[PDB]
Image: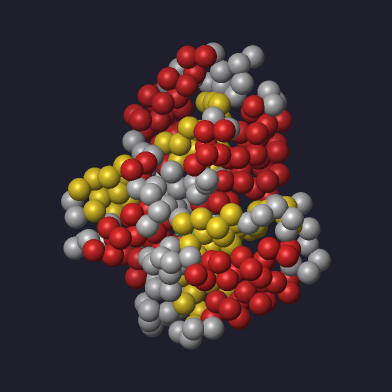
Length: 278
Ligand SMILES: CCCCCCCC/C=C\CCCCCCCC(=O)O
Ligand code: NA
């Protein structure tokens, strides 16, 4: 057969050892910082991108991987005679997945391309479950079906402390019915069917804590398989959320600094709660 090979993009937020252990291939996005282009692959060191974005003259600008890079990576991976499954961030956030579709079509490899409908650790849940099944030698049908199951049992919540990065990066366009006369405000959103749906907005310092208490109430009678927490800036608030959420899931919670691609659009002092239910 040769086992199926899993591909994703560098919007995935994941422990780096897990990438190697499950033979996942990560296609890097890039980001321009004061007119200098960096590969996302060189911005994974804790706090490194944060510090560049804090000091850069210009707001950074993110870029999807080229069609051609996807085609070239798919060609090298299929030399073993295997199929490829590429799982990518939402088409609503990035052209990445369309680039993978074009790349697949240009390559001679047998390549299936799936839109995760998410990013960050929610994309991680799909990718990791795909790679686990791949390495057990499951076929493409079985992998796709289980990955869909993971997706359909996943929720993504995000909190931002400013809207300026979302406005300047354009992804404010995917936020449905948010009215704010202020950019410097705290907002919690749910990413649902490729839209960012606002759940609450507030200037005050308890906006996130109050929202969290409502989340925890709702988790009373859910069976939770995994919780991941991601953050930009310092991890203080993320660690506090972990303390209250860990009681609700057996598996230890991964608390991870999000990547440069997401930090560019969220700004500092953002966070995410990624939940996969049984
Ligand atoms: C703080 C961690 C947040 C994790 C959840 C992110 C949810 C989606 C919201 C904002 C990020 C948007 C990222 C857009 C990247 C585009 C890349 C490109 O094609 O240039
Ligand atoms: Na092909």
